[PDB]
Length: 49
Length: 49
Picture (cartoon, helix red, strand yellow):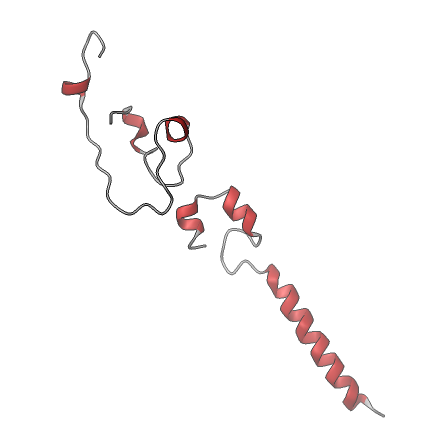
């Protein structure tokens, strides 16, 4: 999935925010790994994607 | 004359009082009441606290 750059902090257990509550929620007992990286050349265009 | 019997009651009530008011110490945690730690702090280290 694709989110805003500032919301990589929001992808964490027990987080509070807008997309965490309404778009995607991570359990507090989550086990695994999280990867985040810029996709401006892919998911961003000057005209707006 | 009979302080030897009063010693038993004094020690018992005194130990009970020490135990009950020992519930107030925070042991280094942020708060001594759990609902405070649960509402005003993030679960992932709320578990540890």
